Figure 1 (tube, helix red, strand yellow):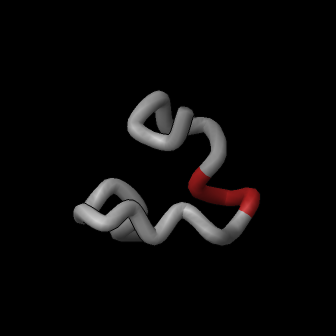
Figure 2 (cartoon, rainbow, N blue to C red):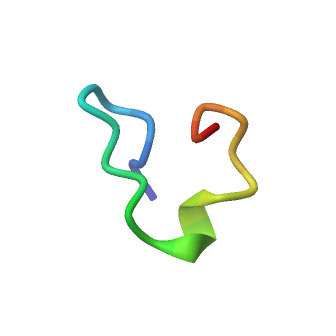
Length: 22
């Protein structure tokens, strides 16, 4: 769920719909 916490832990594709992960 937490993907936008810096440094962004948007490693998973489920975090990709989040514009924080751009």
